[PDB]
Amino acid sequence: LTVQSERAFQKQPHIFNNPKVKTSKRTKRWYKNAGLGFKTPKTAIEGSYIDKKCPFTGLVSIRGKILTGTVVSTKMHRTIVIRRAYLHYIPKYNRYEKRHKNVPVHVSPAFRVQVGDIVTVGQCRPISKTVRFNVVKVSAA
Amino acid sequence: GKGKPRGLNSARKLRVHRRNNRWAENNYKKRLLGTAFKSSPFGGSSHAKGIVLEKLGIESKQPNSAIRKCVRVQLIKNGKKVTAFVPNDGCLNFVDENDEVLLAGFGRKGKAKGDIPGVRFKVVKVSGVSLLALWKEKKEKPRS
Amino acid sequence: ARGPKKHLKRLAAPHHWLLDKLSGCYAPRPSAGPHKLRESLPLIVFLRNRLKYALNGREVKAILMQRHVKVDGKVRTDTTYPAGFMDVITLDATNENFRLVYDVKGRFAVHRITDEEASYKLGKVKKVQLGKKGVPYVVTHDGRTIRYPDPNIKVNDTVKIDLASGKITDFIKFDAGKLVYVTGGRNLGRIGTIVHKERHDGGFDLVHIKDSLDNTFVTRLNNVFVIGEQGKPYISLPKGKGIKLSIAEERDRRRAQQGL
Amino acid sequence: TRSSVLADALNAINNAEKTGKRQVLIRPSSKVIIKFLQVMQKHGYIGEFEYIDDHRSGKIVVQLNGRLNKCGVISPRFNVKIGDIEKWTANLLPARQFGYVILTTSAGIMDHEEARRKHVSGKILGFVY
RNA sequence: GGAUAGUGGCCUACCAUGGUUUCAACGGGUAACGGGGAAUAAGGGUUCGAUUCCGGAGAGGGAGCCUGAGAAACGGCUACCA
RNA sequence: CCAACGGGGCCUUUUUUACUUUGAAAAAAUUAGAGUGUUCAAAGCAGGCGUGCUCGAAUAUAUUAGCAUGGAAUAAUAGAAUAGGACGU
């Protein structure tokens, strides 16, 4: 996709590439590993997208709960909704009932995600009125 | 068998079913609708005070034969109008119009008691003194 | 509330102080200081309720204002100064020294020590970091900051501190086979040796402890305090050596032996 | 629409026992049925039994000796904690000192007394006395 | 980008068309402050909790603000309504 | 010695959940409960012994959700078929 689609120039902050030197190589790119055993995917190291909310190339960090669910909607830009299902115990009747929750979560351009995938998400700081979690691993069902 | 679900995950239907059927219980429905506030003369209290309007005799239901002694009362807090029974025979001489009386329920939770048609309440005190004390000649009543 | 709170109702006080229910409406609120409120011991509670040297809160103040009491070698006069674990208290008249340490029931004991041992205290290392101008420092559990530690000192180690000067003189590494003292949770006051440690990244590490009767138990690493090598404490231990007994054993010992 | 193969089997045994027959045939079999019968056999409530192969879930013939009062299944298979076992025995068994409640546990299928010795729990299957 | 002690449609400009729901959304009622707890119990339950401890809100009704580490304070101030 | 009941090792071709055990957690008062002749009791947390010495202020319970751990019956879920599979040394 076109990287420079916005009205402002997109770049990683404080990453300076110096025209005085003019090495015949890739533009400099910064990345990190999120920890807890999640591997940084190669599309992040070698891609060209700019996304300040990405867990491997943005200014976000992952700490707290880690959750799983199934993808239910992909219609927003860079965000998805997952469904989480569980059983609730009612003591008087000694039996269970089904319930569910919807969680909206941010997804990085490093991942390709489709309805019905199973996804693992990690907690981050508030990044919108509703979003609190970031996609960190994908399994293609 | 037995016409109700048994399955281990059927808890939602069981509790919803019970909620629907409790509305046939007579006293349950009274609480949840708040009937005692919206209607009935004592707005849910055990006693009420009123002003005596006039004095009445009520013919008993057949097969009994008696003219029983009652009064019309207007409740101070509502203005609602009510008929009350006066116990203990000659005690009717102790009550007169524009006296102030304390009333109690006639024991049957809003039903009429015994011979007496449509009378739900009895007098307890008049002008601040109890009828039981007057009848046994233990106190005296000032006029006004 | 529109700001900090100044009062502490009784019943809300920590249970290990052993205040009675009916003597009043309020309890002494500890001042801000080296130790957390929930786990400190105010001086008024020590002098009045434990030692019985004072009958009233009024009398306690008459003692402190004469400067008879010093904590870690310094005179203190605040009635609600928060003493805490491992502190040294000195009363110069009467010529007595105490170290605050736990009973196996989880209460602060009255433990007397010699005039020699009163020279020093132990401290658990809470963090190590570089300060301004690149000078390294350590922080102990009682909030001291000590310049220029030995490069080998790491978090969860224990450090021996001279109360005069305040310098470090020795240290013990956290390792298997060390003696530990348990300072929180259900097992407060027990003593044993480290068997091994469980790593849980992003969570709480757990430590397996064995005591001299070879009972075993588990606690969060936060509650563990290293105090010496196997069989060689760096401090005098309180009576009963941190051995937990069942209620049946306790009943026998009292009435059979002491109950004669 | 057989919802429970185990429920049918114990129902057949009850009806035979009441009328005084000495043998009964049940169809189909399953692993769970075999395990359940072996427990009943150990404590002496039934004789030997024999399995017939047919490439189609098989059949069983059971010998009956007249000692059985009742057997039955509990449905659903409620979860049971170790503290709860004492309540089920009070409701189901006729006395404090004979009869058995039968459980599935990850240690196997067993009666409620063996489960106390081994200190395990799981889910309830049924009862015998 | 602005503002804030600081995150965030918290607010502004431009852009996209999304978000919740028969597993009960949204709307209506409560003579509804939440909890530790209380009464009556074979077991399973039913009813209550303004009130000695913990948390929240308010100072006739609404709005605004000064001082200060901390207040949208009422035994502080300013205006309107009664 | 011997009998029963529990448990470990070895030989014999040798993906994802529910559920259950154990542990840490769940303020004090209240509740159940140990000690102690408030003159008895409801209470309280005290009090004994010679006439300075000394024992105490236990213990249990606390659904569900979250955390760590042992089990693998029962009930689900996944895998090699236009092989595009495994080992490939």
Image (cartoon, coloured by chain):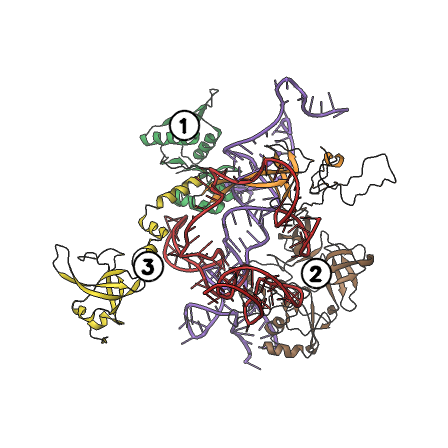
Chain colours: A orange, B yellow, C brown, D green, E red, F purple
Chain for disc number 2: C
Residue at point 33%, 55% (across, down)? B36
Residue A89, compared with residue B55, is above or below; it is: above
Q: Which residue is labeled 3 in the image?
A: B43
Chain for disc number 3: B
- The spot of residue F13 in percent (x, y) is 64, 26
Specify the amino acid type for callout 1: Val
Return the residue nearer the eye: B4 or A126. A126
Label 3: how many residues lie within 10 Å, few (<14), some (14-19) or many (20+)?
A: some
Residue E11, compared with residue C16, is above or below; it is: above
- The spot of residue B19 in percent (x, y) is 39, 44
Of circles 2 and 1, the one toward us is 2
Disc 1 vs disc 3: Cβ atoms closer than 8 Å? no
**Helix, strand or loop at mark 2:** loop
Specify the amino acid type for callout 2: His
Chain for disc number 1: D
Return the residue nearer the eye: D5 or C250. D5
**Helix, strand or loop at mark 1:** strand
**Helix, strand or loop at mark 3:** loop
Q: Is residue F44 left or right of residue B122?
A: right
Residue at point 78%, 60% (across, down)? C170
Q: Which residue is labeled 2 in the image?
A: C141
Return the residue nearer the eye: A85 or D81. A85
Residue at point 66%, 73% (across, down)? C78
Task: Give the Cα distance between marks 2 and 3.
Answer: 65 Å
Tell me the tag on residue D62. Answer: 1
